[PDB]
Image (cartoon, rainbow, N blue to C red; front, top):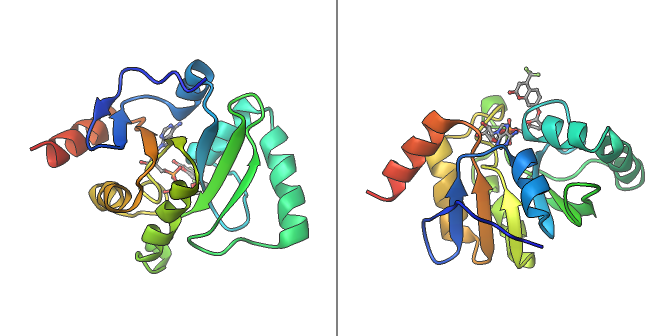
Length: 168
Ligand SMILES: Nc1ncnc2c1ncn2[C@@H]1O[C@H](COP(=O)(O)OP(=O)(O)OC[C@H]2O[C@H](Oc3ccc4c(C(F)(F)F)cc(=O)oc4c3)[C@H](O)[C@@H]2O)[C@@H](O)[C@H]1O
């Protein structure tokens, strides 16, 4: 249905809201919801952990099946799997793990996957356990994605810092 509302428009195509991406998915019912994944699609926490939990582990079983057939993803790569009860499709995207020393330029490649989809509900890739600077991730998203991206930022403190950092 893609009935997004409450988002602050940052650019022609990038929108931001302070919300839980799970809550937004069940209110919006988007065509595509983005997961901030690892290369093994092991959904152990953060966005992935919340999305998986909202699918009742169904997302995890499907993801294991994908990994069993294709093997781990590449950092910066993606794969289109089922959205289950949250969306039509889930676009799993692997941002770089900057904490481990992975190349942050792979964050451009990660966001580039967004361009194959007309509208996405998405988180800030690599901005959590992967330790990428939140402002930088939003900048690469803005500089990279040309389709319509609705970013759900769970943390209010981070949301206010991104809005003022961008719209100011
Ligand atoms: N519900 C939400 N809705 C909207 N936005 C949200 C939401 N929740 C977070 N964000 C925000 O999204 C942005 C991205 O953060 P993420 O950490 O989800 O993604 P990432 O940085 O690209 O790293 C990718 C990895 O994370 C996941 O693995 C883990 C594993 C363990 C933990 C643990 C702990 F078990 F070790 F303790 C604590 C923890 O907090 O997170 C983990 C992530 C996933 O399997 C992948 O391997 C941040 O700005 C965050 O603040």
